[PDB]
Image (cartoon, coloured by chain):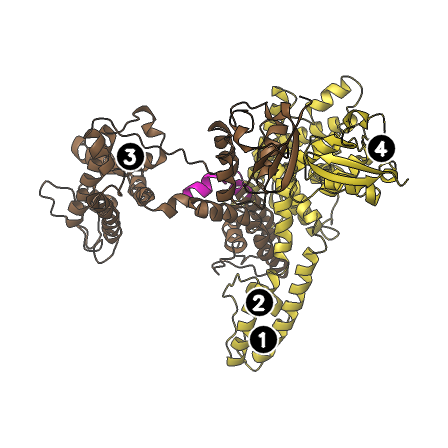
Chain colours: A yellow, B brown
Amino acid sequence: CCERVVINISGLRFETQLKTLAQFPETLLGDPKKRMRYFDPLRNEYFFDRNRPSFDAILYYYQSGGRLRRPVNVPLDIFSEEIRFYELGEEAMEMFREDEGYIKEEERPLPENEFQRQVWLLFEYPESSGPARIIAIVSVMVILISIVSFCLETLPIFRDENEDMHGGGVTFHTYSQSTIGYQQSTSFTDPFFIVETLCIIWFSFEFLVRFFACPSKAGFFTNIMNIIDIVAIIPYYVTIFLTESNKSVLQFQNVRRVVQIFRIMRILRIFKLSRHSKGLQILGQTLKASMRELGLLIFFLFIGVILFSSAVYFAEADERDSQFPSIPDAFWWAVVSMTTVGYGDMVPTTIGGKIVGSLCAIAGVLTIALPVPVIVSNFNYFYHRET
Amino acid sequence: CCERVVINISGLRFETQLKTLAQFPETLLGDPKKRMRYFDPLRNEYFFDRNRPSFDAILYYYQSGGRLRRPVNVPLDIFSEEIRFYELGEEAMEMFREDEGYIKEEERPLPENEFQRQVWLLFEYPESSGPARIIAIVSVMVILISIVSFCLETLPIFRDENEDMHGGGVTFHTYSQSTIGYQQSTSFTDPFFIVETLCIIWFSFEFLVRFFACPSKAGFFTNIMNIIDIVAIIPYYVTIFLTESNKSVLQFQNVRRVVQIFRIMRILRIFKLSRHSKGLQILGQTLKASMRELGLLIFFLFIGVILFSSAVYFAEADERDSQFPSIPDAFWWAVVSMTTVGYGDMVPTTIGGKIVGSLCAIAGVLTIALPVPVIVSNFNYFYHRET
């Protein structure tokens, strides 16, 4: 109880009470059978020829009762080899790394089929083999092929080479060539409509095979990089069900631009690269670690837009020739001028509207730049977090 | 082994076993004949009246077995004079500076001719003499003279004062005055064609003399600042061989704009200043230390371009009067608006196309600024790395 224990770490003395070290009986300093081999009987002390600045954090682990932390001048490779010597446990080591942030609990469980397991690693880890890389090399090239095929449909070398090459009317079958961007047929004479179709065969045979061989079946749809897989393949099928099921009149009066919405939503197939790029996931995590502080930006900009769109609207009010007809006209202008893009479509003209307009140039710097280095410090942190 | 050795560094006492210090027998603490003169027999210790915080890193060099590192509070001038006292070797000093980054292995071997050596330093080091500066003073001025001569060819005080001063047709001899920018002749009445020719005589007599006096002959073309030398002088010769060898008809149908490509590639003669500016090489190294992290920028922008070019194309779709004819038209617009240059050539007009268009102004800040301070921290690091 009152017995004081002198621990000598390479010439540095650390006297402690015996009931402090005996608080933790399974460590090297808590078990008397373990620390028996370090006792110097001529000096009545425990001599450890070990690192010197590491032990003040090891000593205060016992005094505070379990609160250890790394000293500022002791690196992570030196100090982690001291926790393993002093035997502070597998339990107080995990509390140490989480404070540190060296928290990598990734353990890929296989599907357990032993070929359902074996084929799973062929489609989850490119690093297992040469051909494991090849699928990743394929599927990265796959997405690009769809994109160029998607973008070229819009080109007026080819959308002017449509079924309505002159553009006079609108047919129910020409709705696909003008608002779905390809001509669906069992003959499939549309070349892009083939090339569009080819990639979807790859994506499902990625996905469905990845669905049947997943270990976790229920939490499959909480993983975000599986959601993008699903949203990719759908407007393909929405294209076909409009063609296959519908043999009727007056469908455009129900939903026609709703179809044109879907022709956009194809565009988020580009996010499928997230499974392959390490760097794109770091953006995916930086935003995941900034969803409140990003909201500082938008809300500070929403303040900035309204305050100056109005204030320029009334200094540009008394014109018959004003470039600013309303205030939600001037929401376009403010974001052209707080973000300092600056177009020239509409610019203030009056003497007051310039004085208002010039404050808004400064204030957009003072609105973007407040929560930007909040973000970029996270991104820099999440980038090198692999090291 | 069991024996303990007390080392006293200006009143601070470090105790270590004798078999720890005897692990490294050629140092001052490992050789008993060297440390004999520091022994205090009345206290049974080795007394060193030396720096106090330096020795904890010197002591842990012996305990860890060769892992030394500088303490955070001990400067580089103080701590490097302690490694020389404690005699940790020429071998563990080099491992120290590389961790430190004080790695300057530059040793210019001469060409060994003793005048082939001596003239080599006249064209590799401006600091050997006054005239050694003068060649650098000349050649820096040389490059500028070529550039002004290159730019003034394009001027419509002079390209409108061409052989086709009215511009009616195209001759085989007037192709040089209109697509090579000078009139080649043995008379050489074109003044620029002289001035162009004059600089190339300097560049080769730089380069070829630098080629014959190089010590390293095989690795001459791995050094990047020799490649720029080569690519400079070539379209000069491509000009002449087109004039000298060709006496025939119908050569423009084979390659004519390929000649016009070459008239550009003259422009990278400006990189020849890299041999002279210290600062331009720091750019050359910062990019050399960022070729993956720069690829974070382009790939994050390539994502940003495609996503918003499409999303504005469909919100600006249902106009007959739309400024956005296709999506690869709108790649031009996105980079005008993610980089916040902002031109006015084409701007969205619809209510949806502005709401799409205004997100892309914010998101270009959130795409450039993520890997920019990655780069600029390197450039700041490589700038002061000379100190």
Give the image quarter of residue A278: top right
User: Disc 3 marks which residue?
Assistant: B230
Would residue A275 appear left or right of B245 to someone viewing this image?
right
User: Disc 1 marks which residue?
Assistant: A312
Could you classify mark 4 by the number of other residues whose Cα lies within 10 Å: few (under 14), some (14-19), or many (20 or more)?
many
Q: Between residue A384 and residue A349, name the one nearer to us.
A: A384
Q: Nearer the viewer, mark 4 or mark 3?
A: 4
Same subunit, labels 4 and 2: the answer reads yes
Task: State the extent of the magenta-drawn residues as a range.
Answer: B283-296
Q: Secondary structure at mark 1?
A: helix
Chain of residue at mark 4: A
Mark 4 → mark 1, Cα distance in angstroms: 74 Å
What label does residue A30 carry, if any? 4
The extreme top residue here reads: A114
Q: Nearer the viewer, mark 4 or mark 1?
A: 4
Q: Residue flagged by tag 1: what amino acid is it? A: Val
Q: Nearer the viewer, mark 3 or mark 2?
A: 3
Q: Between residue A347 and residue A384, name the one nearer to us.
A: A384
Residue occupying image coordinates x 64% and y 72% = A307
Mark 3 → mark 2, Cα distance in angstroms: 51 Å
User: Disc 2 marks which residue?
Assistant: A333
- For the residues bearing labels 4 and 2, Cβ distance under 8 angstroms: no
Q: Residue flagged by tag 2: what amino acid is it? A: Trp
Asked if residue A290 is among those painted magenta in the image, a careful observer would answer no
In the rendered image, the vertical position of residue B272 relative to residue A139, given as above or below: below
- Residue B204 in the image: state x and y as whole percent: 21, 36
Chain of residue at mark 3: B
- For the residues bearing labels 3 and 1, Cβ distance under 8 angstroms: no
Q: Secondary structure at mark 3?
A: helix
Could you classify mark 1 by the number of other residues whose Cα lies within 10 Å: few (under 14), some (14-19), or many (20 or more)?
many
